[PDB]
Image: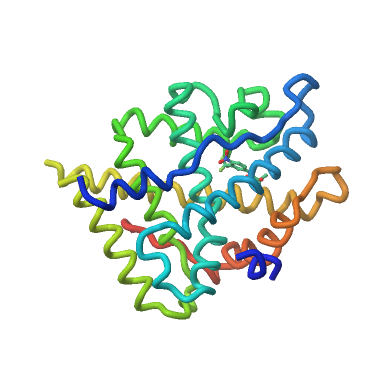
Length: 7
Length: 242
Ligand SMILES: CC(C)(O)C(=O)Nc1ccc([N+](=O)[O-])c(C(F)(F)F)c1
């Protein structure tokens, strides 16, 4: 994800 | 009293604006492009909020990420409703200072039903005389109220973490007994509304290139990847009563 990335 | 209560307070986010042009009239497109943006900003905030939750770094990273994406709408709804209770005594919908809904914005945004529902919730804060500390501890638990039927990566930790969150809510309460059934009743009622909103955003997303509404980076992804899971029964909420 692009979620996994900024988290 | 405890350490716990200091934390929820301390970590509780601040005012978050939507940057809406309160001057031009109320198009659907204008309205919903700002809610999507409001969603986007508050999400960031739920993330930095949640990372600082007590016990939160006990879960597998993927569990953390999951638990957040699944429950964000549910949380959003809750604090929104506190906000609308506390500022405007539940007379209107307080999404943000610059984005307060009135019946007109309610009907023009096309969420009248769901909006009616969330105004009912806001009222319930008042009807049930909800203390600020009851609000915070209730909010904390809502993050732990929604999982895949399949189950999380480290399910034991979750069960544990949650149990202690229910405990703290009971602690901040303790014929008092009926307060719990009420508060659990109240949390339970958050889940239907979050589903209705899931559906509309979902619908909305799909029709969005063809109605001219702006879906931010993080918006488009969460809605199309994780929301469908919920709506297909793969991911259920934990209910207190049946
Ligand atoms: C995805 C959709 C349009 O963005 C949405 O429901 N946005 C949204 C934004 C902010 C807030 N808020 O807490 O003020 C809420 C809601 F939680 F109230 F419903 C929804």
